[PDB]
Image (cartoon, rainbow over all chains, first blue to last red):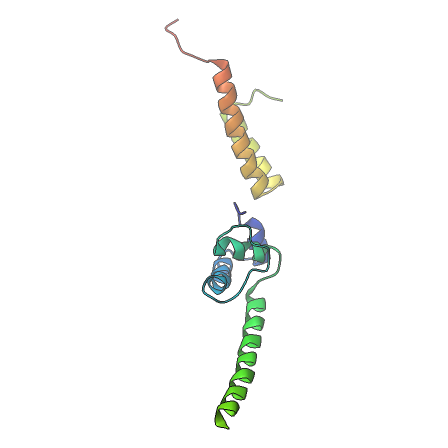
Length: 87
Length: 50
């Protein structure tokens, strides 16, 4: 549950970066991207994103690291797939 | 421990905000409103021509 973002802002110390970060993470979890890191409690995706931010489980750095990992697994699978389609 | 008029209330809220922070102050404001309504009713303060 969520009523204030004071601690979330305490983590990402901007309240303007916080919105952009939470929107990124929430669009991830909303379109078929991912699954929450904090146990969802019948919360909507934005509030889940905030609850994750508060725990220090999400920030800009975390998201970029995760994204580059995703791209690299993408490269690995895609090269293997083209190789398979060859033979 | 005073007679707690309007100004005193507002500065009490301000001091709570400066000492504790946002969340406790918001809960505080809600509690103040509830309890102030409750005892305003209990009082039955009215106004008559006398």
